[PDB]
Length: 23
Length: 21
Image (cartoon, rainbow over all chains, first blue to last red; front, side, top):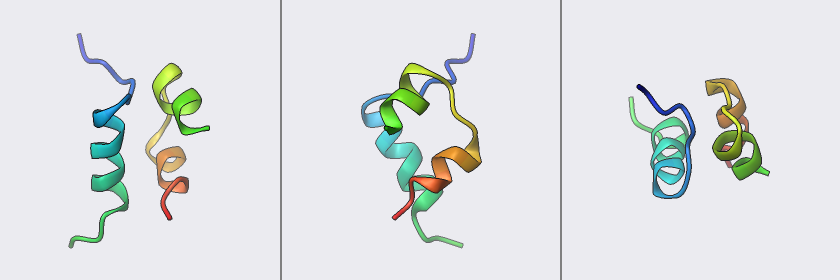
């Protein structure tokens, strides 16, 4: 199974990846 | 807000991207 919900620290991590500026 | 859209429900990459500030 793969959880596609993004909650708590995992949401923060996904926003850091997606929004963070890094080539 | 983002918890309803991405945590309670599943959201797409472009939906999450719109939350970037």
